Image (cartoon, coloured by chain):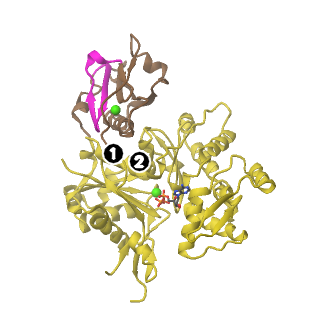
């Protein structure tokens, strides 16, 4: 009986733990910090709190790894400091973004076996793990994290590549947008600690209005929608329509001067790229996942918007699990725990025999 | 992936039912077919005999109202794996307690029953 590890590499946060647990043992920022002017490097929370003397780097952009040296550093830290295991003793399941470049898949594989000497590993698509965590083999996952949002149609366990769509707007952009509109109200948040406050404000008081217009109307006429927020010292700020104006950007990217369509239209578009025969199953299984889908009211709004786009006869079902922030990781925990996982992973032997390219035949 | 139970899967016409039990696919005693624990998740394979002698398959994963996330998730994954094992010849059906398809319900001559309880989660 061997213990498998599960690592969900996100653009903003990394989630790591042991297969079989119902939640990641460690959640920390995806950052590598190094002496800006002159331990040699830090990762995660420590890098973040020592930002005063370190220059921070984020190796994962839009879900894709853009710096392999820094990613290796993150994994090294994950194994030895966060999980406190020797990687050579554990099969490792890693997650990847939809449409992850072929070269990256091989690089990930090479690093695990050659650098970390893992006895076995596997790469699963994040969105698919999330669907499995919801107990379904068919549906369309709307995955929105920190750096990017994806709409991934999946049929009988397999994503449909040609229909996957991407929206380059996610949590990070909403946090930045909140920073800006909050200034119109006079509040200037520009430092890192201030951005943290803004992120907290977004996570704590923001929400998606069922009907934006009507909500603005409401906000402009009475003080019903305002909320108070206590800052780290003691100052108290008053937040108004910014609470729903912030996440509204997900549905109106133009708020950020983006030309692309909102999340609801992207979901509808992905569904329309799929065979007519399976669209019913997608409309009836829209699964939301990722930290950015955590805004209260998003399910209702997605339901409303999708209903407006689909024929009135089509049954629309938005599934928003309370644990969606970690759906991907949980999905991985379950998959890696199956009595059948054993055979699906790439073993060291196989890697030695075929090399990195083996990932294209064993993980699809 | 060739699991012992997969070797037995869809060999001949009939119905086969397995219950998810701590990340594994466990066969349900034939005498108990139709008695579903609402706190559990199951996988059902209905094999039908075809003209050409080949079998037709319908894979149903049944989800009890109180089944834990690991059980419903494992039910879904095992379903994809069995289908792959059967050369992608199975149509998969998600069946939720109290919302089962006419087809699924029709597999049980005497009508399927629900009983409270089940095996503990594997988490
Ligand atoms: N309650 C909440 N309401 C709104 N946003 C939230 C909430 N909790 C977390 N977030 C946001 O979700 C984002 C992090 O999400 P997540 O962990 O899913 O992304 P990631 O894995 O790092 O990103 P990506 O999938 O783009 O790689 C951050 O922008 C964070 O502020
Ligand atoms: Ca993610
Ligand atoms: Ca159970």
Q: Are marks 2 and 1 in contact (CB under 8 Å)?
A: yes
Q: Name the residue under label 2.
A: A129
Residue at the image point whose x is 34% and y is 56% from the top: A25
Q: Earlier in the sequence, mark 2 or mark 1?
A: 2
Q: Is residue A60 above or below residue B56?
A: below
**Whole-number angstrom distance, CA of label 2 to CA of label 1:** 8 Å
Q: Mark 1 lies on which chain?
A: A
How many dots with numbers?
2
Which chain appears brown?
Answer: B
In screen coordinates, is A221 left or right of A107? Answer: right
Q: Identify the image quadrant of residue A158.
A: top left
Residue at the image point whose x is 44% and y is 47% from the top: A130
The question of residue B21 being in magenta is answered with: yes
The question of residue A36 being in magenta is answered with: no
Asked whether the viewer can see residue A167, the reply is no
Q: Residue furthest front?
A: A234
Q: Mark 2 lies on which chain?
A: A
Q: Identify the image quadrant of residue A355.
A: bottom left
Q: Residue B48, image x and y in percent? A: 36, 19
Residue nearer the viewer, A298 or A57: A298
In screen coordinates, is B37 left or right of A249? Answer: left
Q: Residues within 10 Å of mark 2 (few under 14, many from 20)?
A: many
Query: Secondary structure under badge 1?
Result: helix
Residue nearer the viewer, A221 or A5: A221
Chain A, chosen colour in render:
yellow
Q: Residue A163, image x and y in percent? A: 53, 48
Q: Mark 1 points at which residue?
A: A335
Q: Which contiguous range is marked in magenta?
A: B12-34
Q: In this view, does B22 lie above or below A81?
A: above
Label drawn at residue A53: none
């Amino acid at each position: 009986d061997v213990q498998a590890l599960v690592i969900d590499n996100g653009s903003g946060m990394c989630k790591a733990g042991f297969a079989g647990d119902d939640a990641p043992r460690a959640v920390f920022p995806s950052i590598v910090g190094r002496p800006r002017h002159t331990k040699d490097s830090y990762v995660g929370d420590e890098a973040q709190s020592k930002r005063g003397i370190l220059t921070l780097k984020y190796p994962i952009e839009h879900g894709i790894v853009t710096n392999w040296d820094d990613m290796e550093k993150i994994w090294h830290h994950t194994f030895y400091n966060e999980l406190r295991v020797a990687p050579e003793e554990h099969p490792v399941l890693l997650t990847e973004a939809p449409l992850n470049p072929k070269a990256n898949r091989e690089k990930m594989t090479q690093i695990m076996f050659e650098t970390f000497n893992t006895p076995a590993m596997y790469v699963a698509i994040q969105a698919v793990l999330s669907l499995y965590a919801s107990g379904r083999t068919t549906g369309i996952v709307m995955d929105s994290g920190d750096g990017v949002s994806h709409t991934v149609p999946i049929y009988e366990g397999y994503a449909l590549p040609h229909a996957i769509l991407r929206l380059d707007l996610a949590g990070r952009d909403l946090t930045d947008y909140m920073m800006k509109i909050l200034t119109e109200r006079g509040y200037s948040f520009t430092t890192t600690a201030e951005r943290e406050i803004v992120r907290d404000i977004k996570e704590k008081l923001a929400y998606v209005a069922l009907d934006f217009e009507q909500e603005m109307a409401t906000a402009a006429s009475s003080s019903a929608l305002e909320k108070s927020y206590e800052l780290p010292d003691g100052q108290v700020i008053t937040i108004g329509n910014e609470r729903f104006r912030c996440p509204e950007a997900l549905f109106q990217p133009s708020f950020l001067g983006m030309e692309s369509a909102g999340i609801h239209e992207t979901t509808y578009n992905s569904i329309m790229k799929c065979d007519v025969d399976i669209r019913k199953d997608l409309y009836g299984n829209v699964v939301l996942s990722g930290g950015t889908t955590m805004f209260p009211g998003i399910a209702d709004r997605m339901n409303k918007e999708l209903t407006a786009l689909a024929p009135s006869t089509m049954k629309i079902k938005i599934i928003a699990p309370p644990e969606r922030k970690y759906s991907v990781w949980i999905g991985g925990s379950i998959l890696a725990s199956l009595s059948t996982f054993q055979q699906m992973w790439i073993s060291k032997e196989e890697y030695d025999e075929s090399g990195p390219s083996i990932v294209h035949r064993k993980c699809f | 992936v060739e699991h012992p139970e997969f070797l037995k899967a869809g060999k001949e016409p009939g119905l086969q039912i397995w219950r998810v039990e701590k990340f594994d696919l466990v066969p349900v005693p034939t005498n108990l077919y139709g008695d579903f624990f609402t706190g559990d998740a199951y996988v059902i394979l209905k094999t039908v005999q075809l003209r050409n002698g080949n079998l037709q398959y319908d894979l149903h994963y049944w989800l009890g109202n109180e089944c834990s996330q690991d059980e419903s998730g494992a039910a879904a994954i095992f379903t994809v794996q069995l289908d792959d094992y059967l050369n992608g010849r199975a149509v998969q059906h998600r069946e939720v307690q109290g919302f089962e398809s006419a087809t699924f319900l029709g597999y049980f001559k005497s009508g399927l029953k629900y009983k409270k309880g089940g095996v503990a989660s594997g988490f």
